[PDB]
Amino acid sequence: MTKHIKILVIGVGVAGPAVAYWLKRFGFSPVLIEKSAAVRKGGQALDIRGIATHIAKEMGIYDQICNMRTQIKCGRYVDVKGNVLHEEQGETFGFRQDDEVEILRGDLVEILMKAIADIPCEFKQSVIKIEQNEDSVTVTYKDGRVENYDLVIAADGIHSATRGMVFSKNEYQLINLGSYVSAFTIPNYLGLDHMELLCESNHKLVTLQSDSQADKAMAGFMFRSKHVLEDIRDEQEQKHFLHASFQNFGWETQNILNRMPESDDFYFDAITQIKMKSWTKGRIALIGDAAYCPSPLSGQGNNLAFVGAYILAGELKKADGDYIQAFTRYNELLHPFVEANQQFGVWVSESFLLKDDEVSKEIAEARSNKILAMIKSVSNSINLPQYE
Ligand SMILES: Cc1cc2nc3c(=O)[nH]c(=O)nc-3n(C[C@H](O)[C@H](O)[C@H](O)COP(=O)(O)OP(=O)(O)OC[C@H]3O[C@@H](n4cnc5c(N)ncnc54)[C@H](O)[C@@H]3O)c2cc1C
């Protein structure tokens, strides 16, 4: 029966715990593994918008998520001289409305994990080899130990090890949107109070905010550049590149970068999308960022994770565990919605920053209203199946 189907879920992020929840709810018995020692605190702020809110509510975690929501009261577009060009309330500023809500990743994962306390999960575990035939998937762990599963569902992030292990270069594209993103936490030297400031130029923008930690501020950088690092993983090269890339930006960049060396949660990566004709191969399926990351410019990453988790578990349910039928349904039903939200992210990468002109209240406001409407449109551009 479905209960006795062995399913390995790799990655305790959003998609992994999400798909584990729905699989369990739909009569299956999944198990989770995680490379990290434990759930990482805080981190990037995730949007739960569109249909993802409906899924969250059915999961019985929506009120919990709201209890832990970000509490930015005010967002401001400012020029390099610190003048306020355009101001908006927090939710509107983040292009959210209605029941939509923003929550830090770590907080959301903790909530997700509490919702699946009955599901076996093993941290500090890593898969080093995967092999499958028609009957089974053989998983080799770090210590050389081996186990067999009927199915493996990998939710191990945009830099998916599993994707590289299972798929060839012809079976997926890493789509570069010609821009970089960086973020780190610093002392709230400005004394921001549940407020975010955003300053921008023709190719770059810098954000600075404080929210749930009063004596801390989260700095953000987004910019376009065709430059390539000799080693994109080299944190020292990242900080040198970022500093040199913003040396003449003005505004608070000097004050922010002066505090960068002492920040301990530094993050830097290219803005990238994962494009796959098929998210699956035999008994293995990718999900979440590993399968179809829409990049931070889309704001749809979380949305796609929840929807993917719901549909995949659903189609497996309807197929009574027949993964071949389910995986096909998984690819067909979900791709257009993924592609829609990915194209939105691409659009943001190409037209959010003013090409020629300097920002003003009129532009900031019109652009804000336009993005709010458009994101609402794409985030709801799928008709969610009812598996129950
Ligand atoms: C700077 C930034 C800002 C963002 N902003 C937004 C936003 O505003 N709105 C939005 O909707 N989305 C945003 N996103 C995207 C969003 O964070 C993700 O799409 C979402 O968390 C879903 O990710 P996931 O669960 O598929 O994988 P992840 O959240 O990356 O989790 C993967 C998990 O698997 C683990 N793992 C990794 N490799 C392995 C391995 N080999 N073996 C075992 N475990 C492994 C990781 O430690 C992690 O816990 C942003 C992303 C970034 C980087």
Image: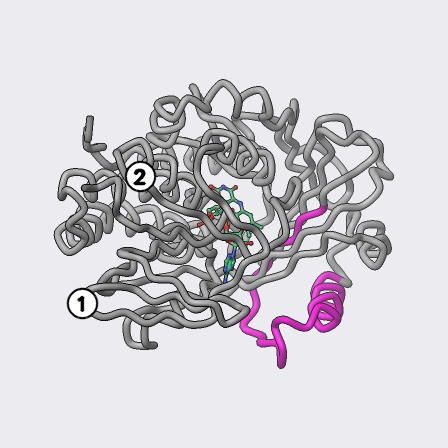
Q: Is 228 within the magenta?
A: yes
Q: Is residue 318 left or right of residue 124?
A: left
Q: In this view, does 347 lie to the left or right of 179?
A: left
Whether ligand 1 has any atom under 8 Å from the Cβ at mark 1 is answered as no
Q: Is 71 within the magenta?
A: no
Write down the residue under mark 2. 23
Q: Give the range drawn in magenta.
A: 219-246
Q: Where is residue 339 in the image (x, y as percent from the top left)?
A: 28, 52
Q: Which SS class for mark 2?
A: helix
Q: Position of residue 92 (x, y in %)?
A: 52, 26
Q: Image height check: is 280 above or below 168? A: above
Q: Are marks 1 and 2 in contact (CB under 8 Å)?
A: no
Q: Say which quarter of the image contains residue 110.
A: top right
Q: Image height check: is 6 above or below 72? A: below
Q: Residue type at mark 1: give it.
A: Glu
Q: How crowded is mark 1: few (under 14 residues within 10 Å), some or many (20 or more)?
A: few
The residue located at (53%, 68%) in the rendering is 142
* Mark seen at residue 224: none
Write down the residue under mark 1. 134
Q: Residue type at mark 2: give it.
A: Leu
- 28 or 63: which is nearer to us? 28
The residue located at (18%, 67%) in the rendering is 134
Between circles 1 and 2, the one closer to the viewer is 1
Would you say residue 15 is visible in this rendering? yes
